[PDB]
Image (cartoon, coloured by chain):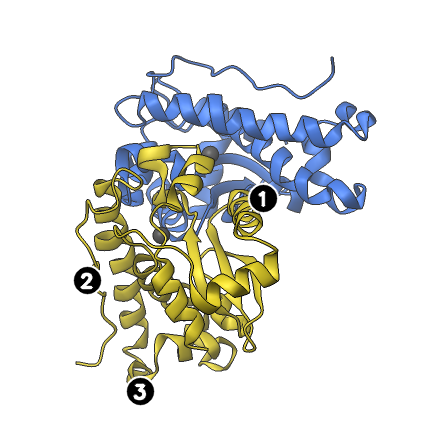
Chain colours: A blue, B yellow
Amino acid sequence: NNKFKVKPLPYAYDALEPYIDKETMKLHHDKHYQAYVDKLNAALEKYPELYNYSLCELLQNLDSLPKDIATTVRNNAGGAYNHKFFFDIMTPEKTIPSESLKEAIDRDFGSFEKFKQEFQKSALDVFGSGWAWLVATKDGKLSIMTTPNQDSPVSKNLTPIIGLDVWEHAYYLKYQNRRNEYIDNWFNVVNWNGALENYKNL
Amino acid sequence: NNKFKVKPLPYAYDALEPYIDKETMKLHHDKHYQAYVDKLNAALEKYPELYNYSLCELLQNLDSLPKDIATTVRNNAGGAYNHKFFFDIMTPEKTIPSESLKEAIDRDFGSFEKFKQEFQKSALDVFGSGWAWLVATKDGKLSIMTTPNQDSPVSKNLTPIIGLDVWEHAYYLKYQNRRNEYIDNWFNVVNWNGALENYKNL
Ligand SMILES: [Fe+3]
Ligand SMILES: [Fe+3]
């Protein structure tokens, strides 16, 4: 069975309290993330060789996939990739920026505080469903960008370093309309060591 | 003061229980709808003559508004118009299709049940944030369509007859990921008399 699979949550479902509630972690991982994976697998039954593509390969070739599944793959491979990435980029452990990522942030944004203010504003300003990202070009230059729905920077040859889900399902149970509070609290759980590994993998 | 205003909810905040929870009615009307109106008013301070346009006129002329506010008006006039419409199209009173709207539904969909199945599927399939609509052309022909985010059929010269908000804020507190249950339950509160008036106003 080479079908796509849901990666088990890398920590306990209540591990990110009180910043993200356990009930939301359960729904977000066990229902939403699961649905993207199930729908993706369903769409590829017609073209089983695509089970041998990685999620990244699917996202990098949306415009050359067979026409009848291009959109469903964009949405569901997007959802699967983004959520796996998102749960991996959070942690109950205490972490801080270090090494080349720490330096790159200062280089490209001036300081960590300036980077943080820009990321928070970009996340706050996403209209509708979507994501805010810290991304790197192939040469390691950092920038902040957003994507709508489950679109991914990977599709634009940009490599995600950290990313924040601002679909309302990600924050409504605890924060309701107060997305600003969700965004601010999320920085307490960002896994900077994972972010560093993402940056090093260029 | 000719600024745009939030229309007071046309019934008690708990009037739509148990189909839509009181807490959601409060947030949806007092926070989300309010924010669209506030942001719209803010954007028009630079062009105060636009306070004399109706919301419909704004939505019908997005591509000819001054370039610097076109997008913010699309989103926020959209939000203001759509929510006023949405709260108006629900009621705690019992209503059923009648008169020309009842006949048009049978004419254009075959039966009410066929109309309902199509509407429910369209609402379920909206990906990301958006709306499902029953709309009419100027000549009274009915169809079902969806819009993303706060885009409106009005901008495409289609007249909304009923419409359902499927942004996650509209259903997450009570239904979480189970949008299907929200959609099915919503038909208990559709105001068919209001829908008839919408259809007659062509
Ligand atoms: Fe999500
Ligand atoms: Fe809404």
Nearest-to-viewer mark from 1 and 3 = 3
Secondary structure of the residue carrying numbered label 1? loop
Place of residue B137 in the rendered image (x, y in percent of width and height, measured from the top left):
56, 73
Nearest-to-viewer mark from 2 and 1 = 2
| Residue where numbered disc 3 is placed | B49
- Kind of residue at disc 1: Asp
On residue B8, the disc is 2
Q: Does residue A159 show up?
A: yes
Secondary structure of the residue carrying numbered label 3? helix
Residue located 33% across and 39% down the image? A183
- Front residue of A126 and A30: A30
Nearest-to-viewer mark from 3 and 2 = 2
Q: Residue furthest bottom?
A: B49
Place of residue B27 in the rendered image (x, y in percent of width and height, measured from the top left):
24, 47
With respect to residue B108, does B111 lie above or below? above
Instruction: Say whether residue A48 is left or right of residue B76.
Output: right
